[PDB]
């Protein structure tokens, strides 16, 4: 695996069983850490760590195609095992963190960020009022196409976010579909799978952990 | 007209008066049917029929630029006469159908589909609850730019859908503008035309059938 | 600075201190006027004036990257000093005007227009009911990413429009954030800046005019 470093005390640990074809990984700064686990396919992506003390953690069996990712100083991106991601954008700044859980499915066109990238202040006392806020995406979350996840949003486990939805606020209820304008729970007590089965979840051995 | 077939009992009937420059039509499977009527211009498009028993019907005088279309087994796309379509995406799966009526105008950036492409099941009994559902777009419908039409949606005749609108549900009232979040009827008893006339529909001979 | 003219009585006044690399400016028609002030950077853009009596006014210190702009007869685009604009689209037709104030920041993916580009008529009397309407963006407005501003919209001074918001209607209150579906005021009595300061607006000498 080839990449560009400018700086020192960086640790780039990419498993020999993983593939990174057509991916550019650039590390500019010091004390940054990259971990890519076994049997990953991180393809046609552009990942830029610019700053110090940055952490990128990608667990085993993760498949990414066409991610554009920018991390700044003291920021963390963690993506857990068996997650798949199509084309999309992740930006982290303001020393923040974004976490994506196990076996998520992120469809084409996601935009996920913990930051507005410019400050907004109160006229009453001058104080900044739009500080960055971490994003937490739970286990087994499916983002439909063209979903935008903004700062501070926490998504519960086993959730479907409907295509073309923008989330500004966190939710607490697991096992639901969230969609609409504004985003709201539109269906409760569900589970999603990858492979289209015509009739029943019991036909899909991969889903036993949810019921 | 050149195209790729892999399979048999396919029928590809493209009128000798129609143009298909820079269009890729791929048929992979058996017993599929393609009809393109007279005086069509189907340009810079990518149309893939992968499966068996697929029907693609495009009537006379249809102009398409930059359509990306995927059809799977037993699916049907029907587009009626004088309809125009700019760049966009149509996906049909789950043995479903999408119909577009006569003299529609689909502006840049449409996404139309009858499927979520992955299953959602009820935790209560395991049953699938997001089966594909047909899409019916009536006669003389105008989709403004960047409109998304999701599964099951039926749009009445002589409707304008405002740009950047997502439709999840069907409507019944013809001769209206639907726009907003959620999509709603914002104007009733109207008719749209193609050519900008400054003052009156009576100046446009092409609109006599609507009043 | 090179450009294409087809027609006469055009005036193309581009300051010798401004840069227009990779920008195509095309003027097709008569009596059109282009002014680009000092120390501008108008880059990788495509600006087409097709018609007569068109005015394009760009003041000093304006930086534009990847604007696609179309103006038709008797239309006006005015962009005031120190405004910055990333990639985006502006369309003006129906002899209308779009104005953008001083020191605005237009993030990637804006779409701004004064026109529906096709007519909608009343069935009751045949009259056109969707005439073009001017767009006025005030001083010190920040459009977040992928914002759409439709015809007739006036935005007050010192406003933030949240990313992925569509505005259909004007607002009157300055010093606010507008976001959501439908767009609404979500925060009042604020001011935004460009450079991320961790704690206070008083640290940014460029903002003294707002409190």
Image (spheres, coloured by chain):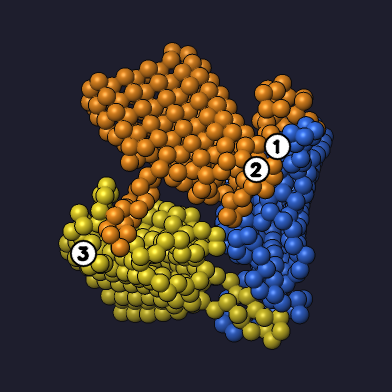
Chain colours: A blue, B yellow, C orange
Whole-number angstrom distance, CA of label 1 to CA of label 2:
8 Å
The structure residue drawn at horizontal position 40% and vertical position 21%, both measured from the top left corner, is: C35
Whole-number angstrom distance, CA of label 3 to CA of label 1:
53 Å
> First in sequence: mark 1 or mark 2?
2
Q: Do the residues labelled 1 and 2 touch (CB within 8 Å)?
A: yes
Name the residue that disc number 1 marks: C190
Q: Do the residues labelled 3 and 1 touch (CB within 8 Å)?
A: no
Left or right position of C8 against A167: left
Q: Where is residue A10 in the image (x, y as percent from the top left)?
A: 79, 37
Looking at the image, residue A31 lies above or below residue A43: above
Q: Where is residue B207 in the image (x, y as percent from the top left)?
A: 23, 62
Left or right position of C135 against C172: left
Whole-number angstrom distance, CA of label 2 to CA of label 3:
46 Å
Chain holding disc 3: B
Q: Position of residue A115 (x, y in %)?
A: 71, 43
Classify 10 Å Cα crowding around label 3: few (below 14), some (14-19), many (20 and above). Answer: few
Res. C177 mark: 2
């Amino acid at each position: 695996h080839m990449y560009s470093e400018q700086g020192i005390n960086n640790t780039i640990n990419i498993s020999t069983t993983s593939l990174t074809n057509a991916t550019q990984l650039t590390v500019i700064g010091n004390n940054n850490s990259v971990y890519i686990g076994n049997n990953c396919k991180i393809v046609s992506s552009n990942i830029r760590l610019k700053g110090n003390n940055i952490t990128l953690f990608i667990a085993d069996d993760v498949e990414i195609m066409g991610l554009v990712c920018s991390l700044h100083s003291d920021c963390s991106l963690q993506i857990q095992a068996k997650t798949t991601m199509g084309n999309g954008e992740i930006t982290i700044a303001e020393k923040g963190k974004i976490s994506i859980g196990k076996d998520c499915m992120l469809a084409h066109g996601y935009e996920i960020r913990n930051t507005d990238m410019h400050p907004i202040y109160s006229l009453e006392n001058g104080e900044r009022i739009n500080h960055g806020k971490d994003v937490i995406i739970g286990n087994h979350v499916w983002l439909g196409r063209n979903v935008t996840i903004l700062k501070g949003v926490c998504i519960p486990n086993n959730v479907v976010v409907g295509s073309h939805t923008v989330l500004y606020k966190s939710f607490k209820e697991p096992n639901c579909v969230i969609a609409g304008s504004p985003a709201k729970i539109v269906k409760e007590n569900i589970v999603w799978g990858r492979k289209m089965y015509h009739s029943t979840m019991y036909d899909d051995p991969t889903l036993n952990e949810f019921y």
